[PDB]
Every structure is written in C-alpha cells, then in structure tokens.
Image: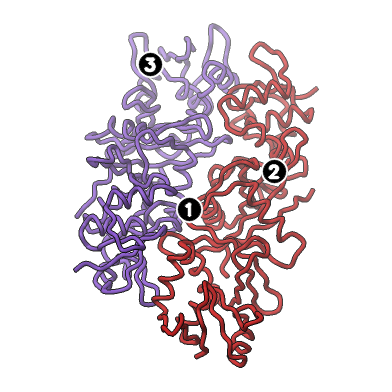
Chain colours: A red, B purple
Amino acid sequence: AAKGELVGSKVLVRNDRDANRLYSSMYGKPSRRGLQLWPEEALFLCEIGRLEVRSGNVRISPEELMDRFVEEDPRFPVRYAVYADLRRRGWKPKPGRKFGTEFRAFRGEDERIAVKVLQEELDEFTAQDILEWLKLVEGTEFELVVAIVDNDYDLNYYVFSELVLGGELPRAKVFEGGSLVSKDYEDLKRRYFGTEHGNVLFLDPFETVYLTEKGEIDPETPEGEPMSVEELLSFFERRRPGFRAGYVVYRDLTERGYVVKSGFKYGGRFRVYEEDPDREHSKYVVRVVEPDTELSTRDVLRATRLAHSVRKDFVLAVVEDVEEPRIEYVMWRWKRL
Amino acid sequence: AAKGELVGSKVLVRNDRDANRLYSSMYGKPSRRGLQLWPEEALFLCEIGRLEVRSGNVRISPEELMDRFVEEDPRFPVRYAVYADLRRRGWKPKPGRKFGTEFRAFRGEDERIAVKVLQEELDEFTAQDILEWLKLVEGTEFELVVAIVDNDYDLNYYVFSELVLGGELPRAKVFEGGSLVSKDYEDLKRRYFGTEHGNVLFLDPFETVYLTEKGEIDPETPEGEPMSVEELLSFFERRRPGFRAGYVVYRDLTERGYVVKSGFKYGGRFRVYEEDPDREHSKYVVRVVEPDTELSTRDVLRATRLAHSVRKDFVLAVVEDVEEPRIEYVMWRWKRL
C-alpha cells in the first residue's frame, strides 16, 4: 500500500512511484510537495487497502479516519456516500470547486458529469438555484447530475437538462370550472380542445382563457355579456393557485402545437402531447413554478419516480416573467449511473 | 320514457308505474307528490333516454338540462362526473347529506360507500378534515371513498381507512446527521438499527434519539459529554422540519417492533417493515402530519400512485398530541370501483 501523511484535511503521498500510480487512476491533485488526496479519496483508498495513513507517527485506521473527517465536516459522510458509489460504479470523481459542484466525474473518453450533492432534509433550494446550477455547465461537455442522499445513505441520481420546445365564433358560457359550448363546437373538439360530454363541449379554465385570447370563442356571462381575457384571468385565479403563470405556459405550449391537458393524474399541472392525444400517450408531465418558488429533494424524487412509472418525461417550467412572457424549461430525469 | 316535471332543481315523476320502476333501480326519493329526482339522477336518466323533462310546457333537452344545472350550481358537473361514472360502473348512488358526503352508493348486497367528491384545484382540506370524514362512517358498513375529479373530468377513487398498529452501552458520537458508533455495535446492527459502512455503524437522527431514550446507546458531544433526549431533539430539529412529531411516530412504530427507515425513495418520511428488512420489502410508506396540516388532492394522487408503483400501502400518521403522545393512522388506497 502507498504511504500517506495526513496534514490538515489532505493526505500527502510523497513517494513518486506511488503518487504516479494513484494519479493514473485519477486520485489526487499534484502539488509542490507531492500528490495531495482529498478526504473522500484518502478514505476510499484506505478502506480498500491501497493507502496507509499516518498523522505524525500515529497510524490512522479507516474507522478513525472516517471519525476525523466527520468531526471536521458534518457533511462529509453525505458527500462520501456519493463519492464511494461513483467509484464503485466505474466513475472517476474529482473533488473541487469547478461548476459549483462537489465533484466532476469522468468515465471512458466521453462521459463527463458535474455532481451536485443534496441531503434529504438539510438542503433547500429554489427554481432559480436550478437555473444557476445549469448555467454553470451550459455549453460544456459536462452534464448536471444531482445526487440525493437519504438519511440512511441510500442514493438517487438525476440528470437536469435544458428543454427547448419545438413548433361567428362559438358561444362559451363561463362558469367556475371553465365554460360550456353547446353549439358549433365540433371544430374545436376535433382540434382536441375541451372535453365532450353527450352533446356539449366543456372547456377547462386555461382552454377558456386561451381560446378567448386567440379569437376562437366568445365567452359570456350568464346575462350574455362578453368577458375579456383579463376578466377571465381575474375570475379564475381567485381560487386557483399560480393561475397566471400556469396560463402563460399553457399558452406557450398550445401556440406551438402541443396539446395540453390536466397533468393531475401523473402528478403535474399539465400532461403534454406532441400531436394526437387519441393516438399517442402524452410525452411530458409539467409543473409550473417561478424563480423564487421553493423546491425540495422530495419534489425531485416524487416527480421523476411518478413520471418514470408511466414512461413520461418530467419538466419544470419556470415562468421568469409573466407579462412578457419569459419561460424556460428544465427536464428532470431519474438516471442509473 | 318516463315523464318528469322540473320544479326548482328537482324532477318530479307523477306516474305511479314509472315512479315505481325508476325507484326499483334506486333512482329518486319518494315524496307526497311523487318520485323526486335529484339533478344528477334526472340528467343521467334524460341522457340515456329513460326520462323526458318539461319545465312548464317546455321540453328541456339533455343539453339544456346540463346548462340549467351548471348555472344553478357551478359544482354540479364535478359531482355529475362521479355520479355518471358510478352508475356506469354498476353502483347505485344516492345523493343526500348522510355522512357529509355527496353520495351514498350501493352495489350488490354487501358494497356500501360514502363518496366524498373533491375537485382538483378548488377543494382544500386538512388532516383534521380527513379524521372528521372518517369519524362519520366509523362503526358503519360504509367505507369512505374519496373521488377526485380533475379539471377535464377524469376520475380517481381512494378508500380512506383506519389503520391500527400491531405489536456499558455503546458510545454514539453525535453529529448533524445522527451519530457514529465505532465499537460494540453488532447487536444494534443485527436488530436492524443503523447503516453499517465498513466497520462503523451510522445511526440516523431518529435512531439516535430513540436509542438514547430507550437506554441502548450513550450519545456524546465531541468533548465526550452526554446529551439528553431533549438536547438531541433540540439539536436535530433546527434544520429538520416536523422533527418532534416525526420522532413520536418513529418511536411508536419501533416500540411495537416495526423496523423504520427513511421513506424518501418511496415518497414518504418513513418506510416501515414488519420484521426483517433483509428478507422482506417494507410494507408501509408513512407521512407524518398534524391535524392542522394543509393537504391537497395532489398529495392523495401522488402518495398513492407512488406507493402503488412499488406495491406498498401509503399511511398518513396524524400526530394529534406530541407530548402524550396521541397518534392516529389513516391508510389511503387507490382503488378501482
């Protein structure tokens, strides 16, 4: 085994031959004094018997080394669970500050990930935080991987990525649940708007606002008066959370030729079809948020596990400005590394 | 077809023969003037051609009847989606106020349900509300069924039910993530406490508090001083939400001989085993709340769909009093009616 000296929180390997051998497996960072191993690297090498560590003239066991590193940094075992698993799974993880992540990890000649480690309970973040994590790896060969560690050190990995999208009126009687179209609705129905029951077409609230804005229906009050788009938004938002932000995402998707319906049954605000709902499964499950919306590890686990169970992609739609509008889409994919 | 007269929001069927025939299929309520049909019943019968409805001398079409009923009560189409589906699925739903539910529904001689209808966005409720819904059917032959209607009138059904549960120290070095036991931990490990890595046992925060309270470990600070149960609760709760309530549920389950671990990966606070985790799958996914905790339709869908995907039962643990403690358990089961 290579011999290392613990100095502060780094383990130095002075022997040139051993340092070269370890570095050829992507352990450590060269330094003026010799190869410097990060705590995760030193502990891993010590546990598998490839490194002996001394502090002064005292041999530090793998158990004592874990103890030391946890005392120095309470987050160490969380990071280390990911480090050791990545090494086990064939990756070469390099601790560092690049990309704002805990590790950059390499596999083969083509696989490159920046690994953001989150603890089940201790790490809070917003949608804006996710945008900022992504921005750091944008235009690079590194994928953003979020590694979530639960309280008992079991792991889940996610790839977060940018999604770029492709792509004489009927009377609509407005009510709390959208609007009712009783006559001349067949065209709208064939274009996948609304839900037909018997010989009446029900439009949901977003469909009602959208088709009004696009000049496809004339919405009316019970007394037969028109309602404006703004009057509809005001009416519907009273008891429906995030309605205006949800609407601009509904409108963006629908403008582009997607078909948008309730995503309730799949755990989202929307389920989204590419073309023909009668023929195809919906492709995306979409949640709408704003930059300051607080998110959780629980959101990431639940959203992706649900989406996976029905073979759909989960998408976070971040409405950055409601009135312009400005919207960005982030896919979350549960991934085996 | 039977002839009915719309009076207010009820349809009266005066013809004794037709009234008797309809009532034999559990439509309507007898009245001094004849059989009185609820809006849901009248519309359903009218849509399937078994009833003709007049208002005064004017024939009201099924489409016009829907229009009238929605204008009178914006929640009608939400209720009606459930009513019509229950009739389709072989149930005989009776509108009324009994049990505080929208319907009592009957099938065969043995199936009896009280159906609580929730709209995807418009209906908010608490854990206390669920306890109150359950209390109304407690000790009766009726099961509590929650029917959730999404914005586009697709449906999901849930059975909510009561769950009644069955059933010289090692040094533990406390840190942010629980505690570390380096020596004499094999007994605790074999009893399924903690997570072994190499030759060290990691105890998570609830395990650390529990095993301290039960006199199974001596927790210590980095300077070697003891910590009390209350000091541990105070330490861990600073950055962990609902910690004290979560702890009393952890303790209740573990006292009874269940094995409790993080439920993160299955969308809960806990995953719970009956006996032997190395042998068995966990049986329950548990979320801990308090009576005033706000819940949503989204919680019900997501929790049960996730639990179903891994063939586990989702359980809501309501901590009604932290200090006594007083805890009740409610199972949520996604069900095909």
Determine which residue is flagged by label 3: B35
Looking at the rendering, which quadrant does residue A189 occupy?
top right
Tag 3 and tag 2, C-beta contact below 8 Å: no
Against B318, residue B285 (above or below) is: below
Q: Label for residue A259?
A: 2
> In this orientation, which residue lies closer to the viewer: A225 or A327?
A327
Q: Are marks 2 and 1 on the same chain?
A: yes
At mark 1, the secondary structure is loop
Q: Are marks 3 and 2 on the same chain?
A: no
At mark 2, the secondary structure is strand
Determine which residue is flagged by label 1: A122
Outermost residue to the bottom: A17
Question: Nearer the N terminus, badge 2 or badge 1?
Answer: 1
What whole-number distance in Å separates the C-alpha atoms at marks 3 and 2?
45 Å
**Residue in the picture at 74% in, 22% down:** A218
Q: Tag 3, which chain?
A: B
What whole-number distance in Å separates the C-alpha atoms at marks 2 and 1?
38 Å
At mark 3, the secondary structure is strand
**Residue in the picture at 63% in, 78% down:** A29
Label 3 amino acid?
Leu
| Residue B170: x %, y % from top left | 25, 68
Looking at the rendering, which quadrant does residue B316 occupy?
top left
Mark yes or no: residue B105 visible: no
Sort mark 1 into few (<14), some (14-19) or many (20+) by Cα contacts within 10 Å: some
Q: Tag 1, which chain?
A: A
**Residue in the picture at 69% in, 36% down:** A193
- Mark 2 against mark 1, which lies toward the viewer? 1
What whole-number distance in Å separates the C-alpha atoms at marks 1 and 3?
62 Å
| Residue B56: x %, y % from top left | 53, 6
